[PDB]
Amino acid sequence: GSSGSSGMNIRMGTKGKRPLRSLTPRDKIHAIQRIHDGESKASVARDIGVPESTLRGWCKNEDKLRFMSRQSATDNLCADALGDKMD
């Protein structure tokens, strides 16, 4: 066996031979199109492995997202959040 999920929270230089937990804003767009093309919200959602709920979030702000890829400042805003309720 082998384990080691210690993790480290340090602010190293803006360069490293490793990926980043966070993802790019363009990634979301990739699928965003599918839905419009023809695919179904659910079909796409599961495609990557996300709850139809979240998915919608992007599609909603898709407008900006489309131009987001061009430039991005930082991820400091909640995409979606609780709202309506079905008794």
Image (cartoon, rainbow, N blue to C red):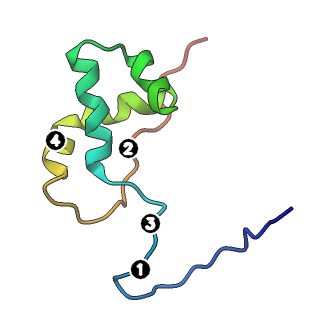
Sequence-first disc among 3 and 2: 3
Query: In the image, which is nearer the foreground, mark 3 or mark 4?
Result: 3
State how far apart marks 3 and 2 are (Cα).
23 Å
What quarter of the picture does the N terminus occupy?
bottom right
Q: Amino acid at mark 1?
A: Gly
Residue 16 disc label: 1
**Tag shown at residue 19:** 3
Report the amino acid beneath label 4. Arg
Seen from this angle, which residue lies furthest front?
Answer: 1
Q: Residue 5: image x %, image y %?
A: 72, 68
Q: CA distance from mark 3 to mark 4?
A: 23 Å
Q: Position of residue 3 (x, y in %)?
A: 80, 66
Name the N-terminal-most of marks 3 and 4. 3
Characterize the local packing of mark 3: few (<14), some (14-19) or many (20 or more) Cα atoms within 10 angstroms: few
Residue 79 got which mark? 2
C-alpha separation, residue under disc 2 versus residue under disc 4: 15 Å
Task: Identify residue for label 4.
Answer: 66
Q: Amino acid at mark 2?
A: Ala
